Amino acid sequence: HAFVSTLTRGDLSSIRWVCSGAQLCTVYYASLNFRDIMLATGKLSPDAIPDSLLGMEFSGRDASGKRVMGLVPAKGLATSVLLSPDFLWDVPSNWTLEEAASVPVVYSTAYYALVVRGRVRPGETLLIHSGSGGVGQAAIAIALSLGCRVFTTVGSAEKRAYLQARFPQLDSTSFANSRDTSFEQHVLWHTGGKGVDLVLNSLAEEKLQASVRCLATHGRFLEIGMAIFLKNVTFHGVLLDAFFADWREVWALVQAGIRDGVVRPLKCTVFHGAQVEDAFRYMAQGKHIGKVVVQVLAEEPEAVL
Amino acid sequence: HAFVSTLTRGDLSSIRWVCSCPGAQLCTVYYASLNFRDIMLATGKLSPDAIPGKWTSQDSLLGMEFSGRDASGKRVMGLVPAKGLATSVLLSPDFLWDVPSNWTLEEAASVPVVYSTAYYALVVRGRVRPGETLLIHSGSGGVGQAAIAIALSLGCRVFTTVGSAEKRAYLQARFPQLDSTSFANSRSFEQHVLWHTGGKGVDLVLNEKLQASVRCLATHGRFLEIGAIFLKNVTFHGVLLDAFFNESSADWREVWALVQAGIRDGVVRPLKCTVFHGAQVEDAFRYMAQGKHIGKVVVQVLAEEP
Ligand SMILES: [Cl-]
Ligand SMILES: [Mg+2]
Ligand SMILES: [Mg+2]
Ligand code: NA
Image (cartoon, rainbow over all chains, first blue to last red):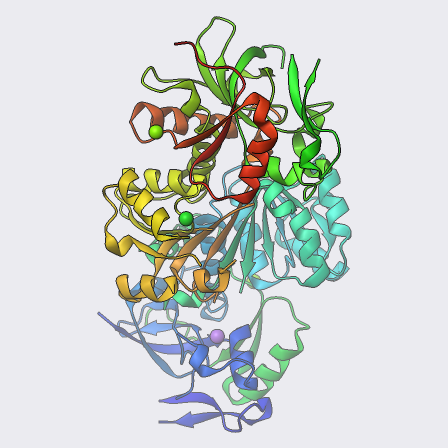
């Protein structure tokens, strides 16, 4: 057994492996999430987390050899994990373990935000900021699966092209800029001045204010961790890791989304286990689209082993 | 036809009576209530431009609430976007309710705003469920009282803050179901609520002591504001009834139906009223502005027949 640790407080360059009804699983792939970077740099305190707390997401095999993926409150960046079966899903036959490790966090977050909290209804109109981000992509897949009208902001033309390739249902009018507030005029015009029913937000300061102005009356503002009253707006603070009966709803939504073809893996950037430091450094640069994953163990050709 | 207008914005001494939807109904106003917005307008603290009913009236925006008779002579009560402080009103029937035979018109004028607001806030927005726990700030205020009635009708556990011992006694008389542990101070309520919920907090807060109130929320709690957040997965609802008044909608009729059912089921009870005759409308505004009452300030435009 080994786990990943920051040997020097706050220094990403010091990231190293250290040898040292619950289900015991062998980890094949462990993904990096934003929280991991915040923990490693000391920007987030371990006390804020509900030895090393790195890693909340993995794919691998259970003791029967079955391919699984899951969420853990901590210690996912390790060679094995022990977790509640309430936080495990079967990996579909059409997925690699590599890509299965990109799924649990972003789709659990997106289903919780859109369905459980936002109560999105078929045909409603959404603004999903930073659509090429992990949670944004998952939210777009879900919204489209419900026949919603989707608007999304992207940080570059390349990110737009990426979303166009991933989601053929998106047309040119689906896209606006995440790097300014021009998405406001865009969304107002294409909704006839009515605005959107839901905003999924990760932006700041002036872009946040512009997002509030984008809401229709009774609009819901989903934040992933005068007008407000005139428009009877609702604001949701959303933090997935707090879950570590509502959760079982999220689990069921993810599972159904997997079976129904809604849940699709992200594109991954893969690092061998010995390059875990590089993986963290890379993740922190934020120049990729999709998931950064660490290959702890290579997947075998066998389906069950 | 006459209506109340402040001839000079911000000067209550300038308050005077001034003589003057295709399926809209004309109603004779017998009683017109005063609401917070009226006082803010009359004292000049609120601009008419902030009011959506500014497009509904061409002169006075005073008065959103009345009881009286429709054209058939039936006793009705209702909401208007503006110009409720008048001898007659023209409004959509979607904003009228029949007055129950056991109510006076006088007290019927105290019902539409506070119960529409509380049903919209607790049920439509807050989605309150039977047995949930609420903290209702300023329970003797109009909306606070209505919210307490609704919560108790659903078998909810109620905590409320009050401004004085007299206001506590008032709530005790009105709501026999409230016990001693229901009350804390609006002027320490955090410690009270935490102790009596075993540190769990409340499911809903109806609400400037926000930091203390937010900390009162159970994880996944809802904060209802009449016009840690992440750790607790909190929801904040901005609530303004007045947005609905300009024209009916399917959204409005849901609230209308809740009030109607609440009336029929004995949940909706008139408030206690302080009545001013029409000729004393200035006194009514001045009184209202001091806020030394419990219940409703109501202007008698016309006495109900004996
Ligand atoms: Cl009070
Ligand atoms: Mg792929
Ligand atoms: Mg009475
Ligand atoms: Na992770």
